[PDB]
Image (cartoon, coloured by chain):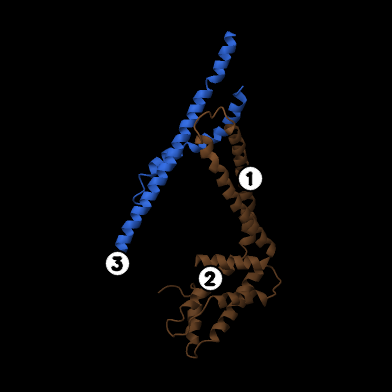
Amino acid sequence: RSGLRGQLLALTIQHEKPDLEEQKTKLLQQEEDKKIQLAKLEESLLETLATSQGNILENKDLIESLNQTKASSALIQESLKESYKLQISLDQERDAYLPLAESASKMYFIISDLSKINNMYRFSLAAFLRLFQRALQNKQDSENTEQRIQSLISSLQHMVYEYICRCLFKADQLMFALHFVRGMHPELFQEN
Amino acid sequence: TPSQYMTFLHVYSAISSSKKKELLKRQSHLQAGVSKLNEAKALVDELNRKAGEQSVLLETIKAAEVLINQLDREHKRWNAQVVEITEELATLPKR
């Protein structure tokens, strides 16, 4: 569940605007490379402490250790400023898609359990992501984006329902409809 | 299956051995660091005084302060892991 949520969230971010996607890619890659290089620069601290354990005040190894620790402190403060300069800059441009991806992760696990009454009701995931591509590629909806999110979940439920009832048997569509409604909105039938 | 019971025991013994050896290596390196830093500080706390005494009866202070400018963060970083690994390798078998 939690993996597929992030997968569809990344697809929606890449299909909303490419600039936010390229930014969230480049910032994360630079943060990872900076973390690896920071571990590499702090990996000489054992050498600067006990590389020979003698004449540490005499040789210039302690002089080069000052330059290395200066580089380490510079990269540490730079990474603090970078992790501050990416958090809210990615949260407000990434959190504008997750109420789509939440119910889109609900629908796949709804239609997964359709095989357990009739065989050959076995559904893939590559065609499902092809459908999730078709939801964008046919939409062309120019509104408020917060007015676009309910539009896209609405025009995705239609395509899911039509794609599954292409396959089904004629005495099974009411089954599929009621189980689908129980899957999407579990609050309108309360308890017991 | 009892084959899984014996696989369990063998991988327990293997992982416990590898982690005991790596924790003893980490405490050895941290102990060597805590020895060398204290020895160099005890050497530098009297050398300029001995030179001043020889000048009183009758050039490493800058690089010592430059080393201390990194050591104020470095020794403060490398301090705590001795007691940390010391309290960690009493909680290795259940892990």
Dot 3 falls on a residue whose secondary structure is: loop
Q: Nearer the viewer, residue A41 or A82?
A: A41
What amino acid is found at the position of numbered circle 2 in the picture?
Ser
Q: Dot 3, how many residues are within 10 Å of its Cα: few (below 14), some (14-19), or many (20+)? A: few
What SS does tag 2 mark?
helix
Mark 1 or mark 3, whichever is nearer to me: 3
Disc sitting over residue B1 in the figure: 3
Chain A: its colour in the image is brown
Q: Percent from the top left, x then y, of residue A143? A: 70, 70
Which of the two marks, 2 or 1, is nearer to us in this view? 1
- Location of residue A101 (image quadrant): bottom right
> Which residue is at 53% across, 39% downward?
A45
- Dividing the image into 4 quarters, which one contains the C terminus of chain A? bottom left
Question: Is residue B95 in sight in this rendering?
Answer: no
Q: Residue at x 48, y 77 (%)?
A: A112
> Which chain hosts label 1?
A
Q: Colour of chain B?
A: blue
Q: Which residue is mark 2?
A: A105
Cα gap from disc 2 to disc 3, whole angstroms: 37 Å
Q: Chain of mark 3?
A: B
- Counting residues from the start of the chain, the first of labels 2 and 1 encountered is 1
Q: Amino acid at mark 1?
A: Glu
Which residue is the extreme one toward the top?
B57
Looking at the rendered structure, the secondary structure element under dot 1 is helix
Question: Marks 2 and 3: CB-CB under 8 Å?
Answer: no
* Residue A114, position as x, y percentages in the image: 46, 81
Q: Amino acid at mark 3?
A: Thr
- Who is closer to the viewer here, A158 or A117? A117
x then y, percent, for residue A18 = 68, 64
